Amino acid sequence: RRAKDKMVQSNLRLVVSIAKKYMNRGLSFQDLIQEGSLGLIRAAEKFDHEKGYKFSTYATWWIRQAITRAIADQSRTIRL
DNA sequence: TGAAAAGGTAAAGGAGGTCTTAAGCTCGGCTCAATTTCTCTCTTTATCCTGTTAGATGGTT
């Protein structure tokens, strides 16, 4: 539990760094951060050390996907 | 006992309702093309879900 907690916790800075690139699309900056946190959690749940890659490369995909999906599902009143 | 005075009866005539036809119409049925619903298949999208491996790591107005 503590290991997963630390993996997510120490990468929130990465989450903020990616989430700052969509601050004018329908979601507030704080919403982008909290939606990308879910992607970071999933990335930390599916990271493979045996792949031999940096976590900052795998986590970016999940963070970006979570934020993009959140924008697609929460930016408009009449959701498309 | 005679005499009003009212009350009847039998007509003629009219008034009114009820019957009859020649002229004409229009109305429904019958057929019969000519089509709009319906109900299956048979697809075909509309909507949702999951994943993505170079590295990246604190805001703008």
Image (spheres, coloured by chain):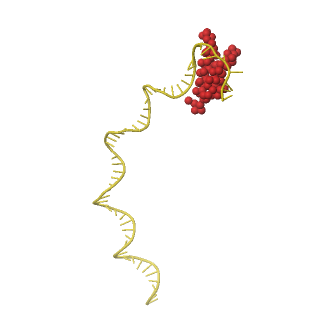
Residue for point 64% across, 23% down: A20
**Along the line of sight, which residue is nearer the eye, A51 or B55?**
B55
**Along the line of sight, which residue is nearer the eye, B55 or A48?**
B55
**Along the line of sight, which residue is nearer the eye, B10 or A8?**
A8
Write down the quadrant of residue B13 in the picture: bottom left
Q: Which chain is yellow?
A: B
**Along the line of sight, which residue is nearer the eye, A70 or B12?**
A70
Tell me, what hue is chain A? red
Write down the quadrant of residue B11 in the picture: bottom left
Q: Quadrant of the C terminus of chain A?
A: top right
Q: Describe residue A17's horizontal placement relative to residue B14 as left or right.
A: right
Q: Is residue A49 above or below residue B41?
A: above
Residue A26 appearing in the image:
yes
Residue positioned most to the right: A2
Residue for point 64% across, 28% down: A28
Label total for image: 0
Residue for point 63% across, 12% down: A54
Q: Quadrant of the N terminus of chain A?
A: top right
Write down the quadrant of residue A69 in the picture: top right
Q: Is residue B43 above or below residue A5?
A: below
Residue for point 64% across, 19% down: A40
Q: Position of residue A42 (x, y in %)?
A: 62, 18
Q: Position of residue A43 (x, y in %)?
A: 62, 17
Q: Position of residue A57 (x, y in %)?
A: 61, 15
Residue A31 appearing in the image:
no
Q: Position of residue B3 (x, y in %)?
A: 44, 88
